[PDB]
Amino acid sequence: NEKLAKKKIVSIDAGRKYFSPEQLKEIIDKAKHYGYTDLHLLVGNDGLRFMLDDMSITANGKTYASDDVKRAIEKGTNDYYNDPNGNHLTESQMTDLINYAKDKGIGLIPTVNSPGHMDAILNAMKELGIQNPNFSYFGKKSARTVDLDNEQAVAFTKALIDKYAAYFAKKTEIFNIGLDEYANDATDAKGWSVLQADKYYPNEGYPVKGYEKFIAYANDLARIVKSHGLKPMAFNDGIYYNSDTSFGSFDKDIIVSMWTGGWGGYDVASSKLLAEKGHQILNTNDAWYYVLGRNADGQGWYNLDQGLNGIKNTPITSVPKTEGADIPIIGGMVAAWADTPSARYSPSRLFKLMRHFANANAEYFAADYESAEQALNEVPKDLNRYTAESVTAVKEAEKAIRSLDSNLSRAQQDTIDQAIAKLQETVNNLTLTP
Ligand SMILES: [Mg+2]
Ligand SMILES: [Mg+2]
Image (cartoon, rainbow, N blue to C red; front, side, top):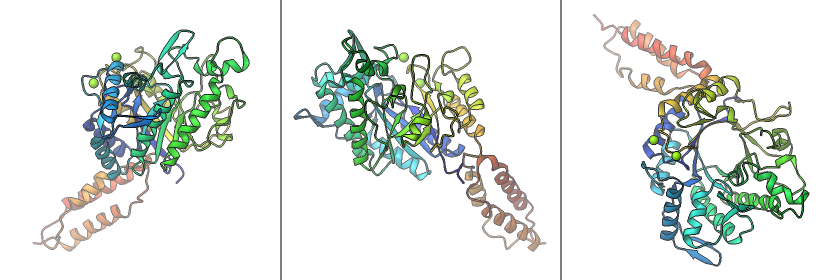
């Protein structure tokens, strides 16, 4: 019961790279088939590839017109990557996609990333006329990250998030605000250290109250998301970075997507600390990451063979940086990324990754009843013309399938499959009364 009740999630980076409604429906079909519960769809992640029908934004003592915001976001996303396959999903397409997923028992969790990984939103703000939205580090400007000292940029960004969250209200349950990898380009992946630095190394030109403002920012987004009845989620790396609780406290209602245990000189809070602070944790271990186009050993970090190895060697219960503690989880999430969005999207490669994650953790993933349902639909409805003995065998086989536990895992798939085979055999053995 506890294993099957977990969320099993596939994450798709449709922020950097365009994915069509058809492509996403196919992913949903596979997710359902392999026993997943949710699709985690990034739509704002460097690029921004989801447009509401009304994109008007009220901030900074004015309203930015819907059509101007749309044109700014379309231009801004293209400036990040002009994808020949498409620019954005429309509101009609999103609503249809969520409905399609819901009818299959699949939830959809969107991401609209900030204050990092927001190249397109920063570009859009510049197109609207907002001045100097980008964070800079000793003259090196981040293409991805907003300056938290810029009230006009921050106000616009929050109102944009609010607008998206208002749309997702009722139709989803979780909204990922991201919060990962602050100014990773401009600081050479040391952004959290940079934001915290002025407190400990004053008068050296580090951002004054940098990390303190980030906490306030994260918390305000959490408040905004919660106002819409949605649970806010965020990636772990900036949450109590360096295990430092002295700058302030994060909203406990933020679910933590735990993707990294950190690296040399990038010292993240342990999952133990985060649990102890009151956060629920979604295991998003980057052991399972796949970057499109990096399709085999040697082709770079998060290549497909690496991800498949991570899936074989790091179970769904193994959370980054536990300090040896027992870390409870709300579920697990395997993630595919489009760091190089011009890479060709290969469905079979993604589905292999998804299939392996489900098979490696089979007790956690729901069994497939699709074919059992179909087999029942294919039984002849009227059996009167057949012998009593052959009829009895069919009715017994039918009962046996309807008697199956409706909460079996992938680990018990063969139980379902044998029941299907037995029904098919009994139907084949139906004998006309002589
Ligand atoms: Mg590219
Ligand atoms: Mg492609």
